[PDB]
Image: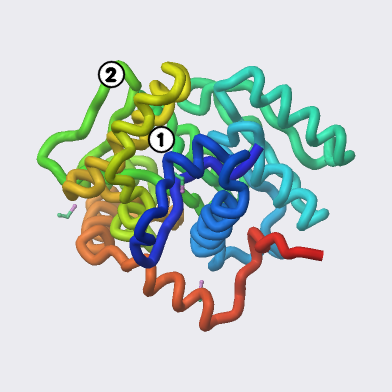
Amino acid sequence: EDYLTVCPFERKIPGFSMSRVILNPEKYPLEREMVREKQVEMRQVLFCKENFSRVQKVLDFGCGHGTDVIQIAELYPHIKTHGFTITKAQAELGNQRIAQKNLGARAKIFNKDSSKDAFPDLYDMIVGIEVSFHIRNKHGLFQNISSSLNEEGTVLLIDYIANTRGPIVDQNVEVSIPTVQEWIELLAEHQLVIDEIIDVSPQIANALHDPDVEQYIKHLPKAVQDLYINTVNQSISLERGWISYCLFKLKKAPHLTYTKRCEWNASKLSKKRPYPEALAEMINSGYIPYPKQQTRT
Ligand code: EMC
Ligand code: EMC
Ligand code: EMC
């Protein structure tokens, strides 16, 4: 029951081991709070151009137990939020927490497959944080997103781009990462253009710099060990430059031609904004609508 994304560090912290902190949160609770603050910060950068007063409906198409679906709805009482998660236990837990907070009239989580089951509404904002690289059928997913996106709406993604000639695929973990060109055409095919693309790769690599991790996790139960090894592999691919971890802010441009959307997306991906730049801009603007950092007392 936490934020489960990787997080950006401006610098490597010597001695800091992400695997020990993530996998032993009861032994390193205050370090886990340090990580949480960076998880929150990265989400703030993702959301900091949205006007939540204008938003009326939000979809999270890989909502896990529904963290943002619940928090957005409780922070903004005029918003209705929907979440899709493939995991039955996560939907049940999310809908329990929705009930425990009396948000059932405005927040609802569905145990459904975002690449196959049609989203039930039209949304002003659609969020997918570390979702789409777990999904094999990319066109089904982005057909679903585009068809449920209001004309003036935004799609917000946190996802990987492959910097290789071909996509980066791994069937045993069912991970598929499109190349730059594949992203250009996938978005353009479904009427979507990149408004902003922010590269977090160096800062994610700083946080995941964990030199003994492969030895450490061999001292953990096979369950744990099997789970975390995908974070290790992404760490390795990030360090090598094979993939990039990015924040996507997309808009719909349906009255525009495919070729024109393609050229736009190409220009944007050739000049990704460094995360420190986007973060400094957010801080200097003073506008940080969601999430808020937790504070003592
Ligand atoms: C992978 C935890 Hg910042
Ligand atoms: C090379 C523009 Hg799609
Ligand atoms: C204008 C900073 Hg999000």
Is residue 94 in view from this perspective?
A: yes
Label total for image: 2
**In the image, ligand 2 is in what quadrant?**
bottom left
Residue sitting nearer the eye, 95 or 149: 95
Coloring scheme used:
rainbow
The residue depicted at 33 percent of the width and 46 percent of the height is 210
Residue 193 in view in this figure: no
Q: Where is residue 25 in the image (x, y as percent from the top left)?
A: 58, 40
The yes-or-no answer for disc 1 within 8 Å of ligand 1 is no
Image quarter where the N terminus lies is top right
| Tag in front: 1 or 2 | 2
Residue at 28% x, 48% y is 258
* Number of residues whose C-alpha sits closer than 10 Å to that of mark 1, classed few (under 14), some (14–19) or many (20 or more): many
Q: Is residue 29 left or right of residue 219?
A: right
For marks 1 and 2, the one nearer the N-term is 1
Classify 10 as above or below 140. Answer: below
Name the residue rendered at 29%, 59% in the picture: 202
Corner quadrant of residue 81: top right
Q: What element carries label 2?
A: loop
| Closer-to-camera residue (162/123) | 162
Cα–Cα span, label 1 and label 2: 15 Å
**Looking at numbered disc 2 in the image, what kind of residue is underneath it?**
Gln
- Find disc 1 in the rendering and name its residue: 132
For numbered disc 1, what is the local secondary structure? helix
Where does residue 216 sit, x and y in percent of width and height?
Answer: 36, 33
Q: Three-letter amino acid code at disc 1? A: Ser
Is residue 68 shown left or right of residue 157?
right
Residue situated furthest left in the rendering:
165
Q: Which mark is residue 171?
A: 2
How far across and how far down the image is residue 55, in percent?
67, 57
Image point 57% across, 59% down: which residue? 37
